Amino acid sequence: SPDGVRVAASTGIDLLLLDDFKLVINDLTYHVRPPKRDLLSHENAATLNDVKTLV
Amino acid sequence: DDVTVVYQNGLPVISVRLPSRRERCQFTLKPISDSVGVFLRQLQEEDRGIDRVAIYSPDGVRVAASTGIDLLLLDDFKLVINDLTYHVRPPKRDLLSHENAATLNDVKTLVQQLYTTLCIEQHQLNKERELIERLEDLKEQLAPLEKVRIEISRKAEKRTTLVLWG
Amino acid sequence: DDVTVVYQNGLPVISVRLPSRRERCQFTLKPISDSVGVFLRQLQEEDRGIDRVAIYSPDGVRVAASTGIDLLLLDDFKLVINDLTYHVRPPKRDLLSHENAATLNDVKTLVQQLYTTLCIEQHQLNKERELIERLEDLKEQLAPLEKVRIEISRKAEKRTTLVLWG
Amino acid sequence: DDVTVVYQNGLPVISVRLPSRRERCQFTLKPISDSVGVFLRQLQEEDRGIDRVAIYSPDGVRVAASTGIDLLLLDDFKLVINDLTYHVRPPKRDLLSHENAATLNDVKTLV
Amino acid sequence: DDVTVVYQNGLPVISVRLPSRRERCQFTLKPISDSVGVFLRQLQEEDRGIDRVAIY
């Protein structure tokens, strides 16, 4: 995690790509930063509706 | 140090301190599909030097392994690593209301229907492949018993033809 | 020589010349079930004289061993056998243009992120739990009634049999 | 004489003429849970007097020793033993599992 | 190509051409402690696509 705490091997992938993290391969730390939607909790009522438009 | 339990995305994440590397580690527990045994296995699998793990109720009794997380996170408890004990105190999240949840269920079921629509053809294809692979094994396993069945049914039919003719 | 990819009966067939046997072989692949790892394993367990084999995207990067075969056959790639490098060009499919594919991708991504952030898995598990609880509650109102229903049925059949014998 | 393939109770069976023991040996084999390799192993274990065995496509390119038998029984093929080459034509069969490549019609019905 | 046998340090080195990588390979044979079976095993162990080996 960006704070330094490890992430258990049972954490789902979809829960991990919601926030940037670090990846340690052997001793190199790559700061992975996935493209996340910058919308908030209420925006779902729009986001869902947004989906409709696309369809 | 300490063990903290917080809530993110509706799921409880619990942050413990592992002994072998002196670093923290957060486990995301599912309050319905997970149990205490699952949490303990995940806790002693992310670190091999945790040969001794336990969870006790705050009064002294040991919590059984077949206990749901939603039943455990109600009251405090004590987690036990190889020789340390941590007094864990879960939080108490708030039930929103009777109105907001009534309008949230619509979205929560529409998203479920949409996700089902997006990923049901590949799942049914895998299911049909598994079903063919399973039927071809069931019939192969049944093949030898049919011989004994027929050898029994011929003797069971001869005597009833004898009964009719008699 | 050369490596070709031809669709036969809707399934891809990759014709490749192996180094040791010096004879051209062909592999039929399922685009849904198999993966790059499965194809590479089949290609290795064919002649046993291939110590290193890989599949590179035309940009230089290497595709993983879990990438599906369907996702790989969209564009060209490079099949690298121990020290040979063959340029594979699968036949192009006629699918959505480069504009509608973006819209469909956006729909898929938004639906998946809504399924994750709203925590629909726990919603479905809670629905199933409520259903189990209702079903098990319906059977606790039946335990007292059936205990007297059985008595009534027994002392009714006990008169029916007596009528028969009479 | 020649080699024949028949489906009985959902399982394919193939009648091979063998050189060392001139007797029509039958092989009942599963199309999904087996490959061509295990079929050649069965042939070699049955005869143990055949120098080699191989399967070829109707054109001449050798078919791999790992393709499933369901992938093979779609079209015709050739079975070559060390001295004879029998053109085997499986029974006419259309579809196996409805699992193939993607199509624009699938995307249309998804939308 | 060809197979050459020469002598170095009193030991015969034999250079064959392996099929799987199209490269040469030299084997140092010991004229007393080695046999033909040992040479064939070493020849089909340095390259896995040599399932058939013989010496006539």
Image (spheres, coloured by chain):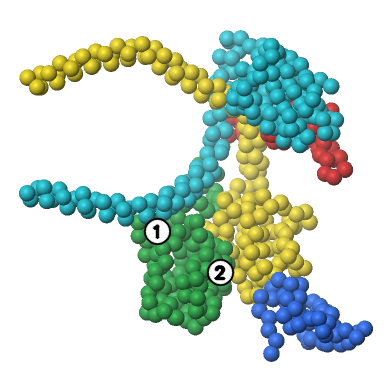
Chain colours: A red, B cyan, C yellow, D green, E blue
Whether residue A3 is visible to the viewer of this picture, yes or no, is: yes
Height in image: C45 above or below B104?
below
The quarter of the displayed image where residue C158 is located: top left
Q: Nearer the viewer, residue C69 or A39?
A: C69
* Residue pictured at 56% horizontal, 38% vertical: B119
* Residue pictured at 68% horizontal, 81% vertical: E53
> Which chain is disc 2 placed on?
D
Q: Disc 1 designates what residue?
A: D11
Quarter of the image with the N terminus of chain B in it: top right
- In what element is the residue under mark 2? strand
Q: Position of residue D64 (x, y in %)?
A: 58, 67
Q: Position of residue A40 (x, y in %)?
A: 72, 22
The quarter of the displayed image where residue E49 is located: bottom right
Kind of residue at badge 2 = Val
Height in image: B108 above or below E44?
above
* Residue pictured at 15% horizontal, 16% vertical: C159
Whether residue C119 is visible to the viewer of this picture, yes or no, is: no
Q: Residues within 10 Å of mark 1 (few under 14, many from 20)?
A: some
Kind of residue at badge 1 = Leu
Q: Residue furthest front?
A: E33
Which one is earlier in the sequence, the residue at label 1 or at label 2? 1
- Which disc is residue B137 wearing? none
**Quick check: do tags 1 and 2 share a chain?**
yes
Q: Position of residue B144 (x, y in %)?
A: 37, 55
Q: Disc 2 designates what residue?
A: D63
